[PDB]
Image (cartoon, rainbow, N blue to C red; front, side, top):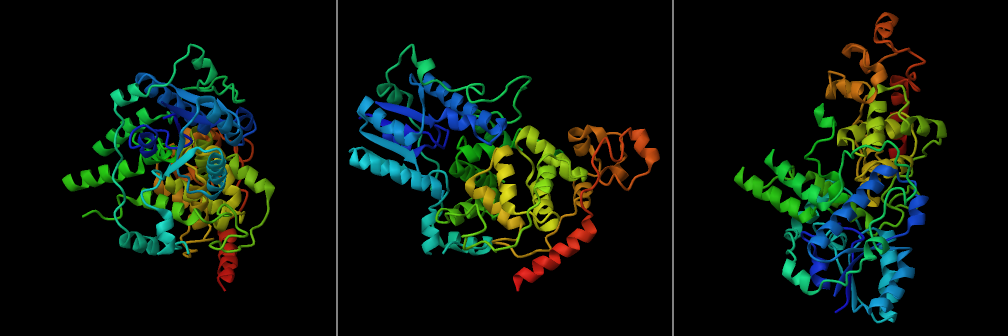
Length: 463
């Protein structure tokens, strides 16, 4: 048959169900390079996508095929491409997200009218999210535990695709193909590349599967680790089911507690809650979200996103996120708490956008979920689960080296004062050679006063 596998997501060949289903097969990614020119998402996540797409082309080229990166909007492209190659069927991995499902319903219909078969497999999640909802979406991590404990075990990693079977259905190779359907570049997509150094989080399934093996084998915690698999799970370079059962296999050599699958269940929990929540990213029109009257301060958001709040632990976290695309989960609770219920009283929706632009592992599902969790807007009620913009830093890194690596103007400050610089002697400031209100910004709020007011406003919302 003439089958098209849409690698819109799950940028992997290992544990790929729809790949085996479609197996003449042509692997397509559809990218609108003008949408990409006007994207608010920064260079780090766009680079990850391209590098991941480059890896599958490299992998497909090993199997005598190539990745067809078609340009344009998907609904306009598929019918002409259907007629161009006489596509017998189109196979794409199912998208839990509502906006994707609405787009996928239109393509599945357009194929139905056009007589093209459509097969969808949701290898992005460990389990069916729609199963759990019938069993209203689970609104607590515990009730969600309870429904997955009543649910069957998640599916095991999927089967491989043979090199001989792939050669049998290898697609037509043209010399012009590397230019026609070749993977785009950052400069093609509107990004300036001058001075761009080697990426901290290299994209692709090859890197991910390599990091899998390195991770299982084993303050710096806050720095990027070669073990880190957060972005590779978000794009699909690594399977949720492979990571689940390879972790299970290591535990058996070392019955599983929930603690190993915490990243995946927290991931799953938000994926379940969002499939049928259309405004999941928004406060209004959202059944699960508390209608908190969040203030609008455009200048606070700016100082928060631009790493200039005066609080070194906050500003160093935002600086790493801007520069590298990944911060530690405890660092995210820090900056989320500062922006929302802890200090600035700005909507979690504003934080969802900044993270979507800068963070490699942001989804519609995982991002809005975490932000509703911190803000105590949903799933969560412990409005005292509080983080000091000073104390949390000194407790995570007493050395202050994290600040020194990402805010080097404060490098000379001694550890006793590096998380709280306004409260430091001008003697030690001048020795550090960092001015109190020139070289670095001063605290834009006072945390003690502000935090007290915000709980009081928070408690009144519960009634």
